[PDB]
Amino acid sequence: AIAGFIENGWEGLIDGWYGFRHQNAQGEGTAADYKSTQSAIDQITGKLNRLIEKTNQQFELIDNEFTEVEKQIGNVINWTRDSITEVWSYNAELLVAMENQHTIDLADSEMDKLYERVKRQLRENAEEDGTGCFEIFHKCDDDCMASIRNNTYDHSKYREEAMQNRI
Amino acid sequence: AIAGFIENGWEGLIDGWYGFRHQNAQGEGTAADYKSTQSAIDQITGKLNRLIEKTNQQFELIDNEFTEVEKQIGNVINWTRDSITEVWSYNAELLVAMENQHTIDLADSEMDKLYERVKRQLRENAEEDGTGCFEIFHKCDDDCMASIRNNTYDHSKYREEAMQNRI
Amino acid sequence: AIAGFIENGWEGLIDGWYGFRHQNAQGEGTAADYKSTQSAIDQITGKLNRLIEKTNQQFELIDNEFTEVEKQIGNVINWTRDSITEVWSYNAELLVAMENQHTIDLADSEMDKLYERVKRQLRENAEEDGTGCFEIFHKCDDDCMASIRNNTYDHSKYREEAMQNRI
Amino acid sequence: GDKICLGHHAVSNGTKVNTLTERGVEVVNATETVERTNIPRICSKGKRTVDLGQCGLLGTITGPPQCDQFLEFSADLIIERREGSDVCYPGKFVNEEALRQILRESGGIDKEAMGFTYSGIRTNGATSSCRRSGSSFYAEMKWLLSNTDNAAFPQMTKSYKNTRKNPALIVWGIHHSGSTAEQTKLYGSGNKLVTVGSSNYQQSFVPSPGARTQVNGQSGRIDFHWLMLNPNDTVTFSFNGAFIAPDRASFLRGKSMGIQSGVQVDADCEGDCYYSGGTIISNLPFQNIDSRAVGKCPRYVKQRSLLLATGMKNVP
Amino acid sequence: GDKICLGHHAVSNGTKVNTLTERGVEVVNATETVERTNIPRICSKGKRTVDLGQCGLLGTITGPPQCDQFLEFSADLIIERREGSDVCYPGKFVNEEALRQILRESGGIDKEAMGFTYSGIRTNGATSSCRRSGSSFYAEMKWLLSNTDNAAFPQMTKSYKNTRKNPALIVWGIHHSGSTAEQTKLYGSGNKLVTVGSSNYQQSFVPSPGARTQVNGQSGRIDFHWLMLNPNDTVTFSFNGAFIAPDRASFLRGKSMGIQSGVQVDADCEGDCYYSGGTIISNLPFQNIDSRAVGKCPRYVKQRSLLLATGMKNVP
Amino acid sequence: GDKICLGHHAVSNGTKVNTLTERGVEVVNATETVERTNIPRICSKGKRTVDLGQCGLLGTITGPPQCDQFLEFSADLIIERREGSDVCYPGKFVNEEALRQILRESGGIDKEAMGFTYSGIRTNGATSSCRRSGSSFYAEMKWLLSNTDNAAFPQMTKSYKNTRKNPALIVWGIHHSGSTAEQTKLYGSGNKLVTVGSSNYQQSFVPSPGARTQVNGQSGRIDFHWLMLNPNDTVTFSFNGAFIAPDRASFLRGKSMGIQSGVQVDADCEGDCYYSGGTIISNLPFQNIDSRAVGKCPRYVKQRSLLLATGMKNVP
Ligand SMILES: *[C@@H]1O[C@H](CO)[C@@H](O[C@@H]2O[C@H](CO)[C@@H](O[C@@H]3O[C@H](CO)[C@@H](O)[C@H](O)[C@@H]3O)[C@H](O)[C@H]2NC(C)=O)[C@H](O)[C@H]1NC(C)=O
Ligand SMILES: *[C@@H]1O[C@H](CO)[C@@H](O[C@@H]2O[C@H](CO)[C@@H](O[C@@H]3O[C@H](CO)[C@@H](O)[C@H](O)[C@@H]3O)[C@H](O)[C@H]2NC(C)=O)[C@H](O)[C@H]1NC(C)=O
Ligand SMILES: *[C@@H]1O[C@H](CO)[C@@H](O[C@@H]2O[C@H](CO)[C@@H](O[C@@H]3O[C@H](CO)[C@@H](O)[C@H](O)[C@@H]3O)[C@H](O)[C@H]2NC(C)=O)[C@H](O)[C@H]1NC(C)=O
Ligand SMILES: *[C@@H]1O[C@H](CO)[C@@H](O)[C@H](O)[C@H]1NC(C)=O
Ligand SMILES: *[C@@H]1O[C@H](CO)[C@@H](O)[C@H](O)[C@H]1NC(C)=O
Ligand SMILES: *[C@@H]1O[C@H](CO)[C@@H](O)[C@H](O)[C@H]1NC(C)=O
Ligand SMILES: *[C@@H]1O[C@H](CO)[C@@H](O)[C@H](O)[C@H]1NC(C)=O
Ligand SMILES: *[C@@H]1O[C@H](CO)[C@@H](O)[C@H](O)[C@H]1NC(C)=O
Ligand SMILES: *[C@@H]1O[C@H](CO)[C@@H](O)[C@H](O)[C@H]1NC(C)=O
């Protein structure tokens, strides 16, 4: 038996992030979805371009390892630096934490957007099983399964048949 | 023929951010939704009040264009300033980027909240076409269309009629 | 009569954050949901662990109340400090504002996740009333109400009965 | 059948903005966050304004000719100019920039006489460098010579209490004569000490005479020193020559802001964040005009522009 | 028919908080993020604590009477007080604040004799300003006079190696006599040099005598100078008068924290972030009490209060 | 009946990351944000590189033996080493670290003769401390003695205009002889002044002779002073002994970066962020290797590691 994303993920889904597991008369299958997988990769790659910048600002020595500077100014420098170190440590931590929270929610949102897309193309010919699948109330051969995936499935073709089987 | 927000936006929607395009016997029409438009404007205006603050802290010269200060302290100042410049540049960039991501998602969420509101008032008398519209399974004259918009549409009035037409 | 979360909250919900108000033949009742309440508390407690850190960095005097330091360096110090004070004030304000926006949306999202969970277990045996309730189209005694809450409700048991009553 | 669509607006020319996730995503509308726009004038409305022009700021204490208008100036906004000079007879202040920093937020200065008087020396030292109606000197200062050429200079002590509630800015000077031949012609033979003590402060000064580069006809030099004399405290000047004595103590009036500039004042436009190029009126939280800008200012950032979205996604 | 509603709690009297998008949106519950609460005592539990009171911190090196308890003090937390004075005979340290900054994180000081001895001069210089059992001096220092009034002062050299592993704080002084009449009575005629060289360090000193403001009966002054003498290095003092010689070198013990304050110690309450008004116990990431606070502290911010929401929206 | 499931990938070994809300939530994939990896070499490809080794940086101006290679060195990247020394005859620069800071971003130095010549004195002062082919001196400097032992030293003035477009680094020195017996043997009796004036600069110098700790056989000391002489300005040296005169002025070439280090150069690997331990090649926005690192660098942070998630939640 077979389950969707509401239960868990698919350790078997190798060539994509998001996908389809179908069960029919011919058997059981898993194909990846390209556009929803790519959209989530691009979004993440966009963060990396932002955060893998190298600073253009140049900084020179103010200080000296070999011959220590006068105490007072050295202490001011050491203090100024530490306050700055505090700031960047805070910023760095918050940024990663904020971005990670968003990276998660971003990807959940992409799963969400695919499932509610399918539900809409399947129209009145299927029901939500609650694990992230649709019980299709008609016969759906490997072709009909492939027409859902590649968003060509026309629901009116199977409507009268399916409608009747839900009653 | 007519489409909703899942496909694209409406270059014709002039007097609101969000709205309704209806198609019936009398013709085709577009009216804006006030409360969902206003809610999104207020939310954005709230950001502007937050970000268009003027700093109350005052800063005085530490430095001198006309008569340059001693090198060592001047270099410390120049260094301190540059580290601060780095910090604000980072903050400014992240803030705009963060706020922009949120401003987008905020507005998508407002469209979302309106559509799933309508779906709920239309009850069992309509179906999701998948472009962001509802195929209403009964006759809906310009009045009935205006009763959906101003959230007065009572679904039980058209129920038995519509239910039957979806079978 | 009774209402759900789309209208407003429940000043009467004492022993949980999220919950169920049912109406049937036996009467009217309110029980809290533990797992969705806990999930939202844990998430919030996670923020507090993050933000109720005490800084490990130590800072020593640079300055002097009793015997004021030379003006120039004192002014540099006073300036450096004020720039740092500006930074933390900005950071502190934004952090609280950002985190508060997220804390709200986090909790809305937890209500959302519970309601759409119920809708899915209730299957074809109930309809969305639009205030955040479900009109169940069969008789649901205090037991059947308790089976929805503790996620044991099997919809096929009441299906043929309910289906028929929605027509 | 009859249908109702849900939609959101859009346009042909979306503005491009950046997000956490995408560079250059189009939105309906966006506003600028980084100020670039500057007014090329000092917007002085609402503020007493002293444009020191020719007069160096430190010059207002000592009083070379340039600064006669300003010996007791009063202001809210103080403007120094590049041409400004603190001197007539060549020289500089020791610790000049601290003192500048003080005077710029001082509200201006109120002068008081310290009441010194003098026996067995001259008082009318003058030079063609500080000229008013021909050879003259620093207004607030007295060039103490010996009584006649080569003559001995009586060892003297002179003091001044600060009876006021606020501290007193005290200033004095040492004269570094262009040769030993000059040092003697003025204050006589022997080596020369000048010793300055408050209680809070002690320090000492020896004149270094010697050939230097000729500056405005002059080969000699005045070192100017200073201190903050405390309420009820006394400053005492023990000296035997080479001493440029103060006539008057200075007191700070109130609060002001000083700036350095190269543009006109304008009392019509109001402002609060100034720089050398002018004034920056703006409500934007950031600016990209000048990192050294001062007053109440937008934070200076590296970037030309950071657009903040004020509308939804564009999908046209 | 039977229905089941989904709901969330609420209250009367939501707390108002700020978000990215709204000012003053009500929530069920919220906690404070900015600390305002201070304990008006120095919470010293767990820490050796020296309350210098009357004794100036720099005074512990030189040893005026105020500081006899502390000539070899040992501490973790050091408290300076407003009344504290580093002197008896008027004077100041040169570079005072650096040296203070050092001693505050020094753990305290351990003294060692430098072993100087003296021929053809006096050693018992004393003054009614530093009094113990009447006229006395700085404990750790020797006021070298000439052998009798007006008498000549033998030119001397004296040295001290630092045989220890750590650096040695070395201190000495110059005497600025109230007149030339005094300078001579003490160290005789002629002008006077004091030259101090380690290897790492060279510098020189001339006494400036002269009338100054009378401070506790005294018109003269002691300049105090210092240096860090390096392991195995030698400091050498070449001098012919006006020299206040060290008896003892100082060594730093360990690590401490110094603070400036105006409230009582309390060894019962524990603490780690101090200020002049007391100590700040708190886990809040920010504080609005005092920007100059020290130790391990919340970051100081401008704002009274920033409430962080710990509950959902209120809709009642 | 037939069903279609929607799913997302997962794995057995999720990487743990932190979020706003959860510590250690697993994700599919995550990248490091904090650089820890360092190359233990100075990556100098693309850059003229001067490894001063034995030669102190300030030594390139004055020219003790160690620095003969470098009296006119030219570079983009300058490397100072711990063994580097700015001297042969014991002494230090006054304001040393400012001057260092200048020379490090100077591109190197181009020397020009100041054209001094001398009558009635000696010019060939030398010492066994600065040895080349036995007793010698600072290359760019002339040790002016009196004409014969104990002999008088003619009071002299000497000057140099800076006719170039850029400022001229000028350096000179004072000789602090190990006794008064030495001071006279070299420059004769009498006390000794050295007075230096540009226009924008005046200052004075007295030699302090006296026993000091013996450093490389030497008990005496050279104070080295400096200034930036302005285009068209003149510096003038009035002196009567104890003066270590410059032969040559120095001019800055262009732009460079200086660093301090303890590892080899490597011209094969390219780099841009250096520290004492080597060079930091990395695109990561932060680093945890060294807070004092310099060049174009990742921001230094406190933390070993901050993992940034590059994949969705793991649910396996
Ligand atoms: C796109 O967004 C911008 C920025 O949000 C819109 O312009 C802004 O509109 C608001 C609404 O009134 C302005 O408030 C006004 O402030 C000004 C100046 O202090 C004042 O003259 C008005 O009486 C009013 O209170 C806001 O300042 C203004 N900002 C700018 C820079 O002009 C713009 O209308 C939006 N674009 C479209 C196509 O709607
Ligand atoms: C509203 O929110 C506040 C803040 O989140 C709630 O108070 C907090 O409740 C938790 C519950 O465990 C406290 O944890 C405690 O930590 C302390 C301090 O280290 C410890 O002594 C306790 O035994 C416990 O572990 C938390 O500290 C506490 N914070 C404060 C400031 O009181 C509050 O309960 C919530 N209000 C309502 C009505 O739910
Ligand atoms: C998990 O995520 C990591 C980090 O994002 C993935 O490794 C990274 O893959 C990207 C995608 O191409 C690499 O991009 C590189 O750009 C540079 C340009 O400077 C170029 O040198 C490379 O040839 C490549 O185009 C990136 O270098 C690489 N990062 C690291 C640290 O190796 C990784 O593939 C993901 N893991 C899995 C199992 O998918
Ligand atoms: C300043 O910082 C370093 C640690 O990076 C330390 O080794 C150095 O001695 C400190 N100096 C002072 C005067 O505190
Ligand atoms: C400091 O920075 C300014 C520009 O911000 C520059 O023109 C100036 O010369 C710098 N001074 C030093 C000593 O680097
Ligand atoms: C520095 O700051 C404090 C207030 O933080 C003030 O009392 C003090 O006098 C200031 N000093 C100077 C020199 O501006
Ligand atoms: C300061 O003035 C008071 C009276 O105003 C005077 O008696 C006193 O001698 C002065 N101060 C001191 C510390 O003596
Ligand atoms: C100290 O160092 C000097 C340096 O020349 C050397 O002569 C001596 O042997 C050293 N003594 C000790 C005890 O380390
Ligand atoms: C500098 O140049 C100008 C003319 O080019 C000249 O008149 C001026 O006097 C020169 N400076 C000196 C000190 O000679």
Image: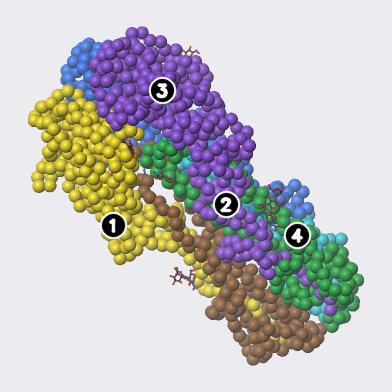
Chain colours: A brown, B green, C cyan, D purple, E blue, F yellow
> From mark 3 to mark 1, how far is it between C-alphas?
56 Å
For label 3, count other residues whose C-alpha is less than 10 Å away and answer few (under 14), some (14-19) or many (20+). Answer: some
What number is the disc on residue B37?
Answer: 4
Residue carrying label 2: D34
> From mark 4 to mark 1, how far is it between C-alphas?
64 Å
Q: How many numbered marks, from 0 up? A: 4
Chain of the residue under the numbered disc 4 shown in the image: B
Q: Residue at x 34, y 38 (%)?
A: A70
Chain of the residue under the numbered disc 1 shown in the image: F
Residue type at the position of mark 2: Val
Please determine whether, in this image, residue E132 is positioned above or below residue C123: above
Residue type at the position of mark 3: Arg
Q: Residue furthest top?
A: D119
Q: Is mark 1 within 8 Å of ligand 5?
A: no
Q: Residue at x 29, y 41 (%)?
A: F162
Q: Nearer the viewer, residue B33 or F125?
A: F125
Q: Residue at x 72, y 58 (%)?
A: B40
Do the dots labelled 2 and 1 sit on one chain? no
Q: Residue furthest bottom?
A: A26
Q: Nearer the viewer, mark 2 or mark 3?
A: 3
Residue D315 image-quadrant placement: bottom right
Q: Nearer the viewer, residue B17 or E313?
A: B17
State whether residue F49 appears in this view: yes
Do the dots labelled 2 and 4 sit on one chain? no
Relative to F90, is E266 on the left or the right?
right
